[PDB]
Length: 151
Length: 401
Length: 51
Image (cartoon, rainbow over all chains, first blue to last red):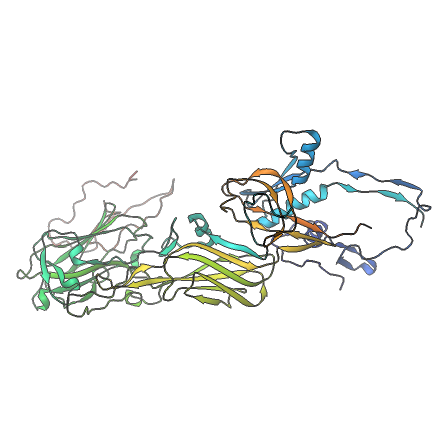
């Protein structure tokens, strides 16, 4: 009853040695970016994100300190994934960040910044697309603010 | 923006192409591990049953001065009569597959002395495989045969030895010579009407003999006409193709193919579960709805003999059905939930799509029929000669407040 | 050649590979009476790689 997969689909990779937390994180990346963990009564859960609200919001009289960056140090805009026995490849390709670096800096061609990685147990190309998409997504620009309050 | 500025290529995301073949390496992938002896040819033109019997009208054999024989119940009205020592009849072929030696056979339709009682010559067969020569004596000095089909390889008729059961490799230049090695009782001729070296197909058909796979008919209508077989090709290859795999349920599937013919027992069979096959008969395109949605599609194909004729042997099955290109499509979700209020769209461009192969790609858009729903600029790339291109289009729904 | 050619014979060499360093033993045996003529006279025997 604690399991509510948002886009339930078959796995086409064998997860047979991954850390359990890393496998669950890949399933959440494949299905609706879900929250998972250990609750009260020590039950596991896996379910849709953003389900409850806290009515006592941090109003302007109720913060004491804040520190709110946009983190982009580790971002990149191309990943090439080798899969099969290293015998086929796929490039996952963010065109927006390449063009924005080009126009910003005045580069003669799109501002590619790459990672190469290899997953030699992946055989379904559409899983190697996931691997590369997941690598870009977890590195992307985000706000990651700290706010301090009391209750 | 109403439309893409010079659109190069367009593909559906209601259907996705889960399998295809159009080239030797693709066909060798989706056929799976066929044995080197299986009577199927993969080629730049398509996949086709192998020629598996040769069958030569006796007047079209290579000649060494043997006696011409004319009778109405001989095929084409005429046969060659083995008579004078060393008067070889010779036949050449190249097999499109490995023939296992324990089921090679040499059917000939043959008689002695216009149906007379008195023995023909003793006859020697030599089979030559690119210079490797195998020789045996199936017909003795004291036998006469009534007009019928006889295998000179696996049986003897007063002779001393059979074919030596050697395998014959694919693409080998194979030559037979059939020779009277000592003289006949009179100037009679041992009349051979038609020679048919073949694979007996007991590997493919559960019977112990070629009669289970070929027509050995023995009556042309007595008027200089022709026999119905042996037909040049196997009756039916029921090919089982490798599973078309999916992450998602398939509710219905559609196929398309190119073929030289679709007559007779030609069909395509599709299943969601590997056993409940639904059949489309005698068509190059078709659609199947499955009993319930399930994730992988299995396929079977039937390729057969075709053609009927009145001017040469064999009168039946002198052509075989070939498939040039194959495509299988399935009703699969390619627009997917991805987060709270977010969808991901995952269209695919097949690796050799004309109008975009060898082309620089610079923009993309989510679309529905003619109307463009979204447009994007892309960093330039060249879609090179073998590359699958696919989308990962996020569409987000959100408020201002 | 006896291995890949035959003269009224029942069977020929199946084309199996010979491993490096394997101990190969070759035997030629008569399996009928001769008609006359001191049999088949074996003058020179040469198992070989045809290259």
